[PDB]
Image: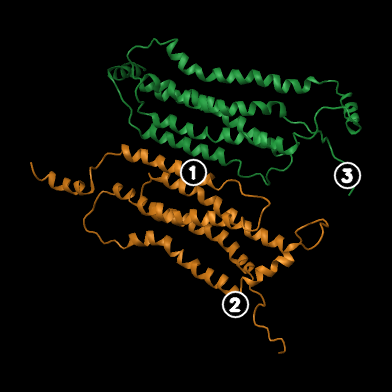
Chain colours: A green, B orange
Amino acid sequence: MKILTQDEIEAHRSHTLKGGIEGALAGFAISAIIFKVLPRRYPKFKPSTLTWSIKTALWITPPTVLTAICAEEASNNFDATMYGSGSSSEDALDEHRRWKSLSTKDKFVEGLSNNKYKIITGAWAASLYGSWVIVNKDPIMTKAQKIVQARMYAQFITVGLLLASVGLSMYENKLHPNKQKVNEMRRWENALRVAEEEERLEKEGRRTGYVSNEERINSKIFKS
Amino acid sequence: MKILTQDEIEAHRSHTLKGGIEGALAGFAISAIIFKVLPRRYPKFKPSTLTWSIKTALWITPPTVLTAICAEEASNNFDATMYGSGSSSEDALDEHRRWKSLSTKDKFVEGLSNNKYKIITGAWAASLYGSWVIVNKDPIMTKAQKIVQARMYAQFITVGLLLASVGLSMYENKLHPNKQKVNEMRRWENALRVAEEEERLEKEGRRTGYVSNEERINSKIFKS
């Protein structure tokens, strides 16, 4: 019946929202450019069906992240009131509340830091094509080992997307986005099957061999 | 007309709640019995990986079908705990829902038919082991080749589960604006990735050349 509100201060990432549209256009450019780095020099990589899978999970993130902008344009009316004197009385007390914080920078670390991480991630991708041209001193060896070696670093740089992804859904949990902890795990248990499935090819798949691999046996039996 | 009674003065769809709980305890029996039929005759194991996945999606289906019981026990009961208000359009709206039917017997086809389909489905499972006990072949052929033949009927008998599934989540959309559904396509596009992935192994498996050539190998060893 008589209950006041608690911390009902209307304030969100409206400042970063402007960048939300700039990131949507960048996702379409780097999306196709990253896949060309390898196939750019060579004609057609036989194992190109691998890089083709990740390209599917990248199209679902950019169109959904937009949900942060539509939530702001709908929540607080952008055309509420411009800047003018008039007779303000309710907003007058809004200033007495910040007199206890005395820290306006609190909102600055939210935008300023974003511009930094924004570029730190873009350079984290080009490191793959720049690592080949800048340096490349390898003798005649099975180039395939490099194709399956990429998996190693990938499995790691990949989790950076999953972890940062769930944290976005668990945040909305505050008000009432859904109910009963469920569904969420759909992407953790599902990514596990498509992952463990690739192993059946490493154990059942027949590997190759050469004159150097057979010579390594002499050093193995040497153990006594 | 002296209150002779008979058995029950009601036949609402809720009458199915009785079998709803009987199914939860029933799967526990067919669950392990169906998996033993094949490995029971085989003195050794091997294809336990293909059978371990199909059994995973079956554990989450039965615990969710219960959503129909907890919904009927609350709905007809006190839905709004605190004093919300009173009756809503559900009273005047029931007028259009009452014309949908014509006779009271219409409620009998709801249960009387459920018992019929309840048996026709139980015989579709045992048909695989009862088909082997028959034993009617003097000569013997490659067994591993038959292990991949089941994939011709399975994928078909499986779709019977997917269709009946979305039909349950799509029916709620009728009168339920609140608590919308997450994303039905979540599973279709997902069931396709884990599916097409199984083909990558069929392209590498090059044991036989063709169905007619496989039988020609018997005469090939005869000629020199």
The reply, left or right, for residue A151 in relation to residue A220 is right
- Vertical position of residue A218 compared to residue A207: above or below: above
- Vertical position of residue A143 compared to residue A64: above or below: above
On residue B108, the disc is none
Q: Residue at x 34, y 23 (%)?
A: A43
- Dot 3: element: loop
What number of labels is visible? 3
Write down the residue under mark 3: A3
* Residue at mark 2 to residue at mark 1: CA–CA distance: 42 Å
On residue B189, the disc is 1
Identify the subunit bearing mark 1: B
Q: Residue at x 59, y 18 (%)?
A: A120
* Residue at mark 3 to residue at mark 1: CA–CA distance: 47 Å
Three-letter amino acid code at the position of disc 1? Glu
Three-letter amino acid code at the position of disc 2? Lys
Quadrant in the picture for residue A103: top right
State the image coordinates of residue B99 (x, y, percent, origin top left).
Answer: 64, 72
Q: Are marks 3 and 1 in contact (CB under 8 Å)?
A: no
Write down the residue under mark 2: B105
> Around disc 1, counting alpha carbons within 10 Å, would you say few (fewer than 14), some (14 to 19), or many (20 or more)?
few
Q: Are marks 2 and 1 in contact (CB under 8 Å)?
A: no
Do the residues at discs 2 and 1 belong to one chain?
A: yes
